[PDB]
Image (tube, coloured by chain):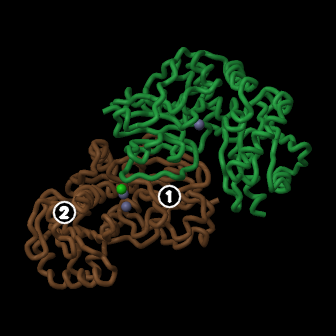
Chain colours: A green, B brown
Amino acid sequence: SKILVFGHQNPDSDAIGSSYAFAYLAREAYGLDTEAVALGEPNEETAFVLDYFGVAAPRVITSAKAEGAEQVILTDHNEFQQSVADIAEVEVYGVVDHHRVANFETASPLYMRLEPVGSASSIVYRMFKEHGVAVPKEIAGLMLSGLISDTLLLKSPTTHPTDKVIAPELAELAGVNLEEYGLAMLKAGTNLASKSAEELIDIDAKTFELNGNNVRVAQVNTVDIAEVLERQAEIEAAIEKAIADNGYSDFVLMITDIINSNSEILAIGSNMDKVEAAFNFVLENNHAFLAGAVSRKKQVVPQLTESFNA
Amino acid sequence: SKILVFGHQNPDSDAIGSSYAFAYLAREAYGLDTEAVALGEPNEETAFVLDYFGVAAPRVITSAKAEGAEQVILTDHNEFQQSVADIAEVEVYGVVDHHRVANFETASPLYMRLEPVGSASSIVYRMFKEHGVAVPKEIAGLMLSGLISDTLLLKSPTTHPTDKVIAPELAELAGVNLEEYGLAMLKAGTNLASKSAEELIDIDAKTFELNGNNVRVAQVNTVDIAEVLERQAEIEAAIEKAIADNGYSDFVLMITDIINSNSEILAIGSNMDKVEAAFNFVLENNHAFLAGAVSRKKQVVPQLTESFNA
Ligand SMILES: [Cl-]
Ligand SMILES: [Zn+2]
Ligand SMILES: [Zn+2]
Ligand SMILES: [Zn+2]
Ligand SMILES: [Zn+2]
């Protein structure tokens, strides 16, 4: 029977790109009856990627059991709360990911291929080369885009030396110029004007427990920090509501400039002294500039973590 | 800094073979400073393997922090309670394994290579091949012996079709005949007569919670079932004591004939009706014959699980 292959809830480009590519690879090289599906519709950055290479969005599902599947393959995630609603009721045949492992468990052995690299799509690509399988131009496009999206065009410190090697091979296969296409697709996910502030602060947001404090950390990509900060009133009203509704001790929003690879940090809550101490900066009107920062998990969360435990 | 590579507590041949082999591969292919260590002394089967190929036992450690390690690599296990005592206090850099995932979590991304095949050694071998790293004769021997040990010379239902393809490749590299070396090494772990009955039932034993009931399932390998049962009285006595002292509802001993691939089941406790039902047999004198049974996790435990649940 069919094995469904999917990325996380609130799919990003790497989630869609990795699962679409892996379902193809599995059919071609592993003898598997796989289908790529998605857990949500594409965001604007991914809608652009899909358009550019002329691939339809993988269909959305909400229950793996409803779709007839007894087995699934997860890509770009493993944590059960990031997965399909009924993940505990199906077998995990396999996982291809680049994140920490938590909230994840199986009854039986499985395939796992995890590497601490820039994207799941990087791993999937290298698996096409291992098995001598040709990469269709549109699948190369999708994988390249996964890698560019997760690392902001190889600028993030989550970029591994192997990523820097495969990026030009992927550009060639995809038929694009690396820097030009990369800039183009990243730009497509920076038009936030038509979204409400509530939506904005929940586009890419997670909660971290830091020495007993529930700290919410969101990120948005932009070509212009000032354009985001010019909506500051409604953003602060959304964040105060979020703090009120959810019991967050603190809310930190990363406003990430994709052109210059820096973030502005807009933060509100009980422990602002610890935010200032984490980054050696001074909040003015709830915000300060953080040079070089584009990775939540490498450049903001560990810094807060240390500071909150100090 | 030195990265420690090791298998699980109470190491079997696969644990030591896969950790020794991977520490070498990681130095040659990944530019890592790895050292293989063990969490216990070799059993009698593994000592035979190590003597055959001219390889010293990996030194035993008890604390990764005492050894000055900050990073470790786990082979043949991932469950924290099967690992080094201070596993929570160091970084898991990588895992290579063929078991289910449980009791396992990391703070950061990592390497994982998991496959539902017959041994971790099988996976390590494939990685040598994938990286173009020539396999030293003694390392092929350690890897082969891990596979043969975990699958009873490829007769276990845990054996994967890829195990059957690699075994002859590994035997040629190791310089041995598959069947004859495999039989010799398996016989080296059947020295039951010089163990007491208390030791015997605890050589390879695990507790499985089956619907509130704590069921102890032990296994021993022998060349002669009837010979093991010459000591039936002292085994039953050791068993009755273990049930009493540990509050097991039931105790199942598999006495596995390595020559013919069958087991005798000797069982004692509150739920024998469910044991008989699990296997379509009648227990006479607390035992019965179970044709084909060599794997506890595939041929004994699921059958008891389903039976213990109606
Ligand atoms: Cl297992
Ligand atoms: Zn993702
Ligand atoms: Zn990703
Ligand atoms: Zn083992
Ligand atoms: Zn093993």
Kind of residue at badge 2:
Ile
Say left or right for A296 vs A36: right
Q: Residue at x 74, y 46 (%)?
A: A299
Q: Are marks 1 and 2 on the same chain?
A: yes
Front position among marks 1 and 2: 1
Residue where numbered disc 2 is placed: B258
Residue where numbered disc 1 is placed: B104
Figure check: A4 above or below B54: above
Under circle 1, the secondary element is loop
Say left or right for B115 vs A60: left
Q: Chain of mark 2?
A: B
Question: Which residue occupies the foreground of this view, B148 or B286?
Answer: B286
Q: Chain of mark 1?
A: B
Residue A179 seen in the current view: no
Ligand 2's quadrant is top right
Q: Residues within 10 Å of mark 1 (few under 14, many from 20)?
A: some
Kind of residue at badge 1:
Phe
Under circle 2, the secondary element is loop
Look at the numbered disc 2 and say if its residue's Cβ is closer than 8 Å to ligand 5: no
